Amino acid sequence: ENLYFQGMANIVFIATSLDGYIADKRGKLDWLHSVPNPNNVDTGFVALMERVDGLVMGRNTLDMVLSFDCDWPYSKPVFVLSNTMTEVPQGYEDKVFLVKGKLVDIIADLNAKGFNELYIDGGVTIQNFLKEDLIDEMVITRFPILLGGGVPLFGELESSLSFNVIKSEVVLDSLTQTTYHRKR
Amino acid sequence: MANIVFIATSLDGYIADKRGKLDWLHSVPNPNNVDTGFVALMERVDGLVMGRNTLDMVLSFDCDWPYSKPVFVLSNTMTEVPQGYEDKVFLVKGKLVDIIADLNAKGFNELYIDGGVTIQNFLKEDLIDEMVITRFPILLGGGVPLFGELESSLSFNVIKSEVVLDSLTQTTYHRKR
Image (tube, rainbow over all chains, first blue to last red; front, side):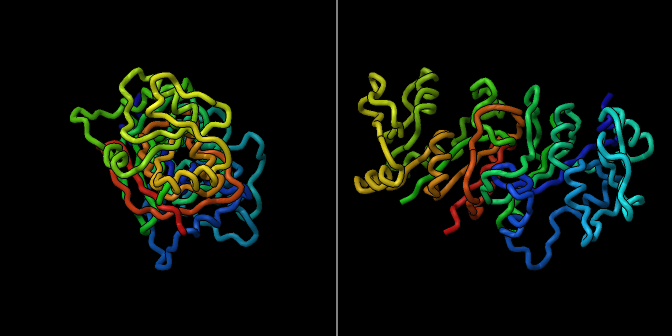
């Protein structure tokens, strides 16, 4: 019963195109540079990372973040959902931790260990959370570009899921950033 | 001279739900019947361009014709207009660039483009100048999408964004020329 009100939250924080893609058809994020940010203005990430206890991420996102030329961007543990992945690559054993099983169980287990506020990342992972109605908050930064193909943020659902608008503002002059909480 | 989209969408980008229905549009209360741009839009535009799907949806509401301006239905199959709508609805056939050229020449210069399939076809030829999207806070998880495929991306500028009726966001995008 009501883990959110008891202080446990699953939080989405993601950039999408106008048409709902989180990567283009080549798996790239170059379109994120379609809007200038010369002065390196922060639009929520430092504060998200300070708030969350860890991340739950899919293998597709992990594989795109892991690289030879990579500066690991996360200050909190990344829990990676793979039925497929048996071991964490060299250099990332204190950064990335494997979790397996039913989402509800995985979440119960992390929460019991004190990882109560989780940053849920990755399209398949987010979609899977939403299929069990496990997302409490989403902050979506929408870019004024139609990509016309790519990796979708959202998928299919058994029934519609309603949210409240907590806040919406224009950031960096040409982005909208809207904060949704799931309706109780 | 402008081709303008003015449409409501779910958070996940649908313009009708998985059953073809629009109930989710009455999920945000509007007891005072506030205008969220439609009246000012109809005043501005010279006409509408829509397709068979939107025509049929409007006719399905069993209400008074809502449009003060002529409605052009873009269709390469329809040859006759629904009975009673001969003074209201006109068919246009052929290449889009030609259709727009012919309408503009007749003084139909500001056009409200409606319909998923029609908007998509304008987008595939980069013929959309402005879009006002009113986004509802609901994941439908299925339905009729607003957007489809493009060969290549299209960039816009955010002219304005605001919360309307407390729970909706309404953003005005102009095509980056």
